[PDB]
Image (cartoon, rainbow, N blue to C red; front, side):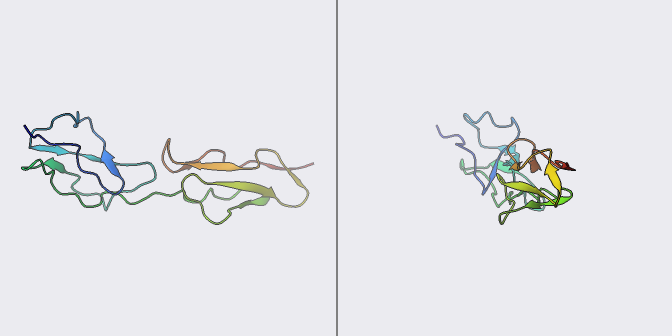
Length: 129
């Protein structure tokens, strides 16, 4: 007649495990949480969304935070340009020092929606010609 509904929703958290089925949960289910790309949980504790008593799933705090891109690092013989922030979905432009020609790329992308905070194309080259 009732059963547990669309489970609890946290600031960036969403169920990881095929615990769910997410159809009709009978009251009494401990489920586990997954943070979205570019998020970190709280200090990583009891990740327990129980279907409690009153189809009112149990505790729900803030099991996420955020993981933004941690700087594309530094290129070489030259330097790397950050227009004021390297968050998720960002990017840079490579600029070599004097006398050199960029032989690798003139940009690279911050993407998190694949393998967590990572960048596409690391060190190009700066080849003096």
